[PDB]
Amino acid sequence: EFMLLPNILLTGTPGVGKTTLGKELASKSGLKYINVGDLAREEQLYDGYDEEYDCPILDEDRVVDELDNQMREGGVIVDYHGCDFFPERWFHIVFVLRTDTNVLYERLETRGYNEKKLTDNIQCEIFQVLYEEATASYKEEIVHQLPSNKPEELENNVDQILKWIEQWIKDHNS
Ligand SMILES: Nc1ncnc2c1ncn2[C@H]1C[C@H](O)[C@@H](COP(=O)(O)OP(=O)(O)O)O1
């Protein structure tokens, strides 16, 4: 198997559907799915603790070092609720999943988030923080917002991205 394969970033507020989409994409394309939070947990890539948010702080440099070789080889779908620290060269396309605030709140409430965590996350979405972070970090032409409210939308997202992957592979393996 000697094909050039693309790298895809799935970003957006926690709860929007990144993991659901990334896992389905991996199963249906054979690309490797990487959950950055899970990777950080497995490889213990943390430095410091945030007092106000009550969470260990992701060690961004170590995450980058951990992933770099694999990213260089291509064919990776990366899922994280942040994107400014990734090398720009990693990604061929970046999707920012978006979820209506009312819908997102019900999802995050079901997760058992307390009030402070619910509020911070919900404001993150309503202020469009990750969308702005993606646009600030990557070329406008490769950043796309995806609706992620209903199963029908997940289905459309899977379909559109699978079609994009197929076209990209053709274009970069002449
Ligand atoms: N497009 C969609 N329509 C309806 N429910 C969705 C959806 N995408 C995800 N979900 C559900 C699955 C989970 O119960 C919840 C959060 O999904 P997720 O994949 O864990 O989000 P994230 O990885 O962005 O935090 O929403």
Image (tube, grey):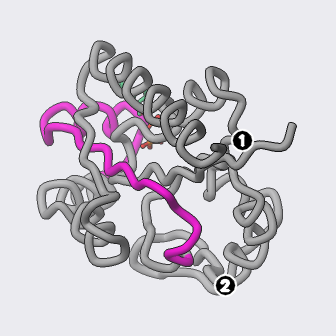
Percent coordinates x, y for residue 81 in the rendering? 43, 59
Q: Quadrant of residue 86?
A: bottom right
Q: Quadrant of the C terminus?
A: top right
- Judging by the rendered image, the residue that carries numbered circle 1 is 32
Percent coordinates x, y for residue 88 in the rendering? 49, 75
Please identify the residue farthest to the top as the structure is shown: 152
Q: Earlier in the sequence, mark 1 or mark 2?
A: 1
Q: Residue at x 30, y 72 (%)?
A: 133
Q: Which residues are magenta?
A: 87-114
Q: Residue at x 50, y 30 (%)?
A: 20
Q: Is residue 110 above or below residue 53?
A: above
Q: Quadrant of the N terminus?
A: top right
Percent coordinates x, y for residue 26 in the rendering? 64, 31
- Judging by the rendered image, the residue that carries numbered circle 2 is 61
Q: Is residue 62 above or below residue 96?
A: below
Q: Residue at x 21, y 53 (%)?
A: 122
Q: Residue at x 57, y 36 (%)?
A: 170
Q: Which residue type does callout 1 highlight?
A: Lys
Q: Dot 1 surroundings within 10 Å: few (below 14), some, or many (20 or more)?
A: some
Describe the element under mark 2 as helix, strand or loop: helix
Q: Which residue type does callout 2 highlight?
A: Asp
- Residue 173 vs residue 141, the one in the foreground: 173
